[PDB]
Length: 80
Image: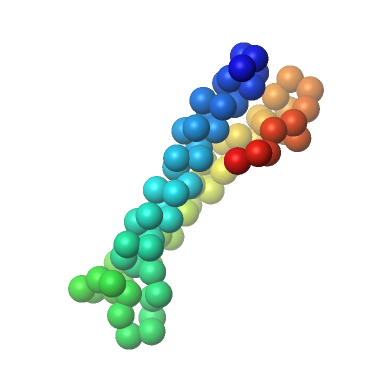
């Protein structure tokens, strides 16, 4: 792979493996919340945890603001 595609791939591999990890934790527990049980003993911390996870993930979302710049273009690879 070319270095630019290689870097976005190794960035992408880091990013893609990250997206399922959030899904794996949510599906395992702290899903289906507020309807009398959320696969947890407390069911209150899970809402805070996912909100806490999202806020830095949105900070992770905002830290690729350079991808709009990169060198000249962004929308070259959106395969996965």
